[PDB]
Image (tube, rainbow, N blue to C red; front, side):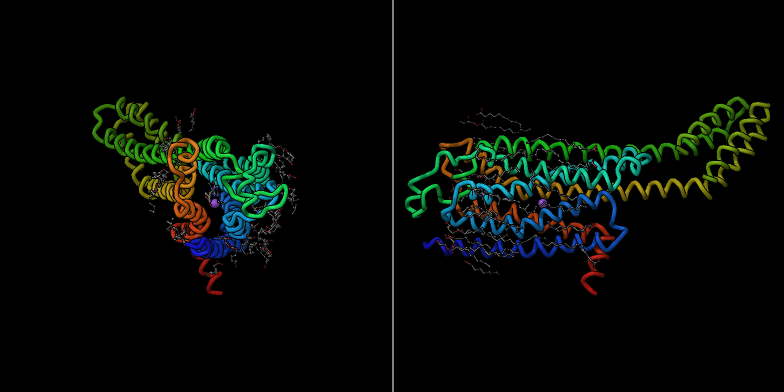
Length: 383
Ligand SMILES: CC(C)CCC[C@@H](C)[C@H]1CC[C@H]2[C@@H]3CC=C4C[C@@H](O)CC[C@]4(C)[C@H]3CC[C@]12C
Ligand SMILES: CC(C)CCC[C@@H](C)[C@H]1CC[C@H]2[C@@H]3CC=C4C[C@@H](O)CC[C@]4(C)[C@H]3CC[C@]12C
Ligand SMILES: CC(C)CCC[C@@H](C)[C@H]1CC[C@H]2[C@@H]3CC=C4C[C@@H](O)CC[C@]4(C)[C@H]3CC[C@]12C
Ligand SMILES: CC(C)CCC[C@@H](C)[C@H]1CC[C@H]2[C@@H]3CC=C4C[C@@H](O)CC[C@]4(C)[C@H]3CC[C@]12C
Ligand SMILES: CCn1c(=O)c2c(nc(/C=C/c3ccc(O)c(O)c3)n2C)n(CC)c1=O
Ligand SMILES: CCCCCCCC/C=C/CCCCCCCC(=O)O
Ligand SMILES: CCCCCCCC/C=C\CCCCCCCC(=O)O
Ligand SMILES: CCCCCCCC/C=C\CCCCCCCC(=O)O
Ligand code: NA
C-alpha cells in the first residue's frame, strides 16, 4: 500500500492531539494566572508541566510528523528534531518529581513549609530543571549519535545530497542512549523515586491520622479511668497522662482551658481530694465537646484534603508512566533482542501517539479532581 495512506492517518491523529494539548494546557496556564487561590508553589510546577505539554503540540508533534517522512536533511539538524521531545519529557519528569517532593514537605514538616518552599526558590528550581532538561535531552548532539555512520544506501535511494541523511529517529539517535541513558537513568529511576516519595506521603498521612484518633481515644479513656478511680493517686496518674497528651496535641483558647483544667484537677489530686479532683475532671468534657472535637475534625479534614491532593498528583505521574512506557519498552526489545523482528510500523506509530496523548490528559485530571481548577475553568469558558 502507498506510504501516504497510513501516513495520513498517523499525521491526522497527531494533529488532533496537538490541538487538544495546546488548548487544554493553555487553559491550565490561564487559570493559574487569573486565580490567586491557584497561585502557590505546587502550581508553579504544574504550569511548567503545562508549558512543556504546550510545546509538545507546537513543536514536538510537528517534529514527529517531519521525522516520520524520512526527508533528506543534514544529520545534526535531523538530530535536533529527533531529540527535542526528549527535552520536554525530561522537563515533565523534573516537574512531576518536584510536585511529589513539594507535597511530601507539606505533609511531613507543615510548620516549616512556607519558610522552606517559596515562590522565589520554586522559580529558580524550574529554571535549573529546564537547563538540565536541555542538557539531558540534547546529549546526542554532543557526539553520542550515529551521524558518523550514515546509511548511505538509504540516503542515495532518497536522492539526498552530500552530508545529508534520510531523517529517521532510529537512524540518528543511538538505541543504547535511548535505553540506558534516557530510559533507565533519566526516566525509570526518577519515576521509581516518585513512587517512593508518594509511599512516604501516604504512610505519613496514615500515621498522623492514626495519631489523632489515638490521642482522642487516650483523652476519653483516661476520663473514664478518673471516673471509676478509688483513690487520689489513681486520678493523679491518669491526669499526668492527659497533661502530656494535651501539650503534645497542642504542638489555642481551647487547649489553654484544657491544660488549665487538668492542672486544677491535678492540684486537688495531690492534696488527696479525690472527689473534688474527679468533679473538676468532669469539666473537661465541656471543654472537649466545645473545642477539642472541633480541632480534631478540622485536622482530620485537612489531612484528608492532603491525601486527596496527593492522590491527584500521583495519578498524573502514573499516567505519564502509562503513556510513555510502551514506547520505551519497544526500544528495549529493539535494543536487547536483535534476534527479534522489529516491532511493526503501526505499533510504533501507536506507541508514539500514546506518548503524545499524555500532553492532553492533565487538564482533565485537574478539572475532575481539583475544585478550584474546575470552577476556574468554568468561569473562563463561560465568559
Ligand atoms: C521559536 C521557535 C518556534 C523556533 C523553531 C525553529 C525550528 C523549527 C528550526 C530550528 C532548527 C531547524 C533545523 C536546523 C537544520 C536542519 C537541517 C536541514 O537540512 C533541514 C532542516 C533542519 C532539520 C531544520 C528544521 C527546522 C528547525 C528545527
Ligand atoms: C530562541 C533562540 C534562543 C534560539 C536558540 C536555538 C538555536 C540557536 C539552535 C536550535 C537548533 C539549532 C540547530 C540544530 C541543528 C543544526 C544543523 C547543523 O548541521 C548545523 C547547526 C544547526 C543549524 C543548529 C544551529 C543552532 C540552532 C538553530
Ligand atoms: C505499561 C504497559 C501498559 C506496557 C504494555 C507492554 C507493551 C509495550 C509490550 C507487550 C507485548 C510486547 C510485544 C511482544 C512481542 C514483540 C515481538 C518482537 O519481535 C518485537 C517486540 C514486540 C512487538 C513487543 C513490543 C512491546 C509490547 C507490545
Ligand atoms: C518497574 C518496571 C515497569 C520497569 C520496566 C520494565 C522493563 C525494563 C522490562 C519489562 C519487560 C522486559 C523485556 C522482556 C523481554 C525481553 C526479550 C529479551 O530477548 C531481551 C530483554 C527484553 C526485551 C526485556 C527488556 C526489559 C523489559 C522491557
Ligand atoms: C521517546 C522518543 N522517541 C522514540 O524513542 C522514537 C520515536 N520514533 C521512533 C521510531 C520510529 C520508527 C521506527 C522504525 C521505522 O521503520 C520508522 O519508519 C519509524 N522511536 C523509537 N520518537 C517519535 C519521533 C520518539 O519520540
Ligand atoms: C548532563 C548533566 C550535567 C550536570 C551538570 C552539573 C551542574 C549542576 C549544577 C547545580 C545547580 C545549582 C545552581 C545554583 C546557582 C546559584 C543559586 C544560589 O544563589 O544559591
Ligand atoms: C503553531 C504552529 C504549529 C506547527 C504548524 C505547522 C503544521 C504542520 C506540521 C508538520 C509539518 C511537517 C512538514 C513536512 C516535512 C517535509 C516532508 C518532506 O520534505 O519530505
Ligand atoms: C549544559 C548544562 C550543564 C548543566 C547546567 C547546570 C544548571 C545551572 C543553570 C543555571 C542556574 C540559574 C538559576 C539560578 C538562580 C535561582 C536558584 C534558586 O533560586 O534556587
Ligand atoms: Na508531560
